[PDB]
Image (spheres, helix red, strand yellow):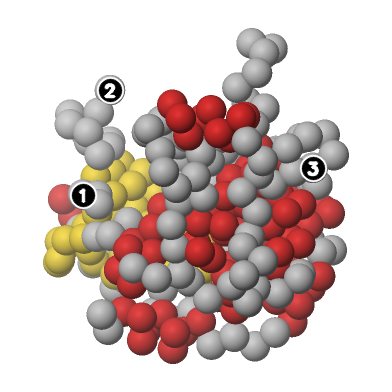
């Protein structure tokens, strides 16, 4: 092992686990598994070989981080056991062609920021890889971050300057803009390079004043996409922002929405 589920840490082996179905949107290979010892169904990611995700295994008490049960090693893989989620956000954007509603993106922002905040505070971590593949939603309305600390547009304006987490705030901005609208925020692209150019090159791709987004939403997104990184806000700051304040507070049935969007 070990598998730690439900407060107790257990010795375990991947072959000991019963394999059911395979997934997923996430691509994986991600597996659906059962741990005979406690009865729980879970998700196992299997990857090929050549780490310190110990932390996601230590972040059981943040409800916006996807729960990590434990890690397994072999000849070939490298198995990661985790709580099972419904899907990625990237998959949702494609699975519906259109944009994702602000009320959902609002709930998501709250979850995303509070998770990023926890990581920094509880374990002085900088997620880095903040983007729609890293935002998981479920049948039951939960929204969570994972894993791994292009990967191109999501690049901040700094972070490609001198060889010397506002970078994460940036990536948050980009994803939002991308997930709000329904198309990447740097549309016509000569991949990888033109993209990175524009980031440093043009003016931060704020939210269309055209589409019916609120002024708190457009304001959240704008502060995130602050080119000067120094005058860009910390998590402490965004958490006081009215977009977040509103969305901590506001009933939004993410559950039924997710369910319904699924049926397509």
Kindly state the secondary structure of the residue where label 1 is placed. loop
Q: How far apart are marks 2 and 1 (CA)?
A: 17 Å
Task: Choose top left, top right, bottom left or bottom right for residue 257.
Answer: bottom left
Element at label 3: loop
Is there CB contact under 8 Å for labels 1 and 3? Answer: no
* Left or right, residue 210 beside residue 84: right
Looking at the rendered image, the disc whose residue lies closer to the viewer, 1 or 3, is 3
**Pointer 3 residue:** 232
Q: Are marks 2 and 3 in contact (CB under 8 Å)?
A: no
Image quarter in which the C terminus is found: bottom left
Q: Mark 2 points at which residue?
A: 50
Nearer to me, 96 or 5: 96
Q: Which of 52 and 237 is in front in this view?
A: 237
- Marks 1 and 3 sit apart, C-alpha to C-alpha, by 38 Å
Identify which residue is drawn at 46% across, 30% down: 194
Quick one: label 1 or label 3, which is nearer the N terminus?
1
Q: Residue 29 carries which label?
A: 1
Please tell me in which quadrant of the rendered image residue 35 appears: bottom left
What crowding class fits label 2: few (fewer than 14 Cα within 10 Å), some (14-19), or many (20 or more)? few
């Amino acid at each position: 092992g070990y598998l730690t589920i439900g407060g107790q840490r257990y010795q375990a082996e991947i072959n000991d686990l019963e394999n059911l179905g395979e997934m997923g949107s996430g691509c994986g290979q991600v597996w659906k598994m059962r741990f005979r010892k406690t009865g729980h169904v879970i998700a196992v990611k299997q990857m090929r070989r050549s780490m310190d995700l110990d932390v996601v295994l230590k972040s059981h008490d943040c409800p916006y981080i996807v729960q990590c049960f434990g890690t397994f090693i072999t000849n070939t893989d490298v198995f990661i056991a985790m709580e099972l989620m419904g899907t990625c956000a990237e998959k949702l954007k494609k699975r519906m062609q259109g944009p994702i509603p602000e009320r959902i993106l609002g709930k998501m922002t709250v979850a995303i920021v509070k998770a990023l905040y926890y990581l920094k505070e509880k374990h002085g971590v900088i997620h880095r890889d903040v983007k729609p593949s890293n935002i998981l939603l479920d049948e039951r309305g939960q929204i969570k971050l994972c894993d791994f600390g292009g990967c191109a547009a999501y690049m901040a304006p700094e972070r490609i300057d001198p060889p010397d987490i506002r970078a994460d705030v940036w990536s948050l901005g980009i994803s939002l803009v991308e997930l709000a609208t329904g198309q990447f925020p740097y549309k016509n692209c000569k991949t990888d390079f033109e993209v990175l150019t524009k980031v440093l090159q043009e003016e931060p791709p704020l939210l269309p004043g055209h589409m019916g987004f609120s002024g708190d939403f457009q304001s959240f997104v704008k502060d995130c996409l602050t080119k000067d990184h120094r005058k860009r806000p910390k998590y402490n700051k965004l958490l006081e922002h009215s977009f977040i304040k509103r969305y901590e507070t506001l009933e939004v049935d993410v559950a039924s929405w997710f369910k319904d969007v699924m049926a397509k």
